[PDB]
Length: 208
Length: 208
Ligand SMILES: *[C@@H]1O[C@H](CO[C@@H]2O[C@@H](C)[C@@H](O)[C@@H](O)[C@@H]2O)[C@@H](O[C@@H]2O[C@H](CO)[C@@H](O[C@@H]3O[C@H](CO[C@H]4O[C@H](CO)[C@@H](O)[C@H](O)[C@@H]4O[C@@H]4O[C@H](CO)[C@@H](O)[C@H](O)[C@H]4NC(C)=O)[C@@H](O)[C@H](O[C@H]4O[C@H](CO)[C@@H](O)[C@H](O)[C@@H]4O[C@@H]4O[C@H](CO)[C@@H](O)[C@H](O)[C@H]4NC(C)=O)[C@@H]3O)[C@H](O)[C@H]2NC(C)=O)[C@H](O)[C@H]1NC(C)=O
Image (cartoon, rainbow over all chains, first blue to last red):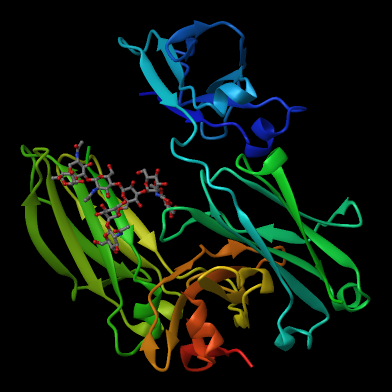
């Protein structure tokens, strides 16, 4: 028995005109007893034909994996068009279909509050910079830390949590040496989201 | 063929003498034809017999569901013992075993810092109080907010996120009326983890 998993593009990919957002249809456990598969693709039902079926990853525990990949228009995903993936096989007397779309609902723009380190943390050598990103919908989003135009590396980001009103929040924690913070370096939480003007915003953080 | 599931106790259960931790073994998709199942329980390979086995329950999908519950000792779970669940049937060629234990790995004491709201958030009629809880292992943990010994409610907490240095961090966000914050009310983030003294700590957050 074989299985399908339909996969949404990256946030950053659909929000940046430079990039190529992609729907990743995934079939796992295609045995050697019937290794040939097929893919049909649909956009509001309309059959499309710009779909690269990239072969054919092998696997450790004696399984396989055949993945199709459809490129998509940024404003066709953002408008919310449903992307259907008709999979076909001889090991399946009926086609398995799997459909996805962007989270329906009114897009709510993020509020972004950066947060200084705790007085209690200045004891240590490194120090935490906190980024509150709250009130957004859908949950698709991108955060990055930077300083003086370059990225920061030691940052980590929580997944987005369903908040009480029905929007989302998440936090980001950039870790930097107490020395860079006290020296007066300025840092930025950078947020990419669909309901932001120009799909992005940036908040500053600096010990004045 | 039937499936077996093995669920650990809640974190709070294994940190509080006041609570009773337990391991629960659920078995779904038990046939109507070959319906009798049998639990044998092992703790570090030693059979135990204090396991309680609730009566079979016919599901609205024509399959049966039996549950076995084993009461474990607090230190036993904390000392990282393996609990094995051996489920038996004739419909099975061999029994099904499932085994579970605490996250092996040297435990780490959570650092807990509370951060006030951004100044930019005082325009809203509610405000956001933040609890950073970082550098804890294992990732089993519990985070309550409260004020004047009474619970709070309107809070949401992130999942624990794997930080760069192998430990975990999370954020808990308590949302209060701006008036309550500004009036000088003091709030508390209480935290439960195995690596804390008395398995507990609280941090205060007030305006002054
Ligand atoms: C016939 O019916 C029964 C029951 O259906 C119910 O009753 C009938 C009458 C109808 O009314 C239905 O509407 C109603 O739903 C069906 O039984 C189901 O069978 C499936 C598997 O086929 C089980 O899936 C597993 O679910 C667990 C989580 O289950 C807990 O949370 C559920 C909500 O998500 C909740 O509904 C469950 O009751 C259960 O509740 C927990 O209870 C314990 C003890 O009682 C308690 O300690 C907890 O507090 C409580 N938890 C919660 C959240 O309330 C899920 O975790 C499993 O996922 C693992 O396995 C998946 C694939 O099997 C995998 O994809 C997942 O990622 C995950 O994989 C694991 O991942 C972990 C960590 O990520 C890792 O450590 C493991 O290695 C890895 N394990 C493996 C092997 O994968 C899993 O999805 C349902 O629980 C079960 N429902 C019930 C109520 O029993 C039955 O299928 C029906 N038959 C048919 C064919 O129709």
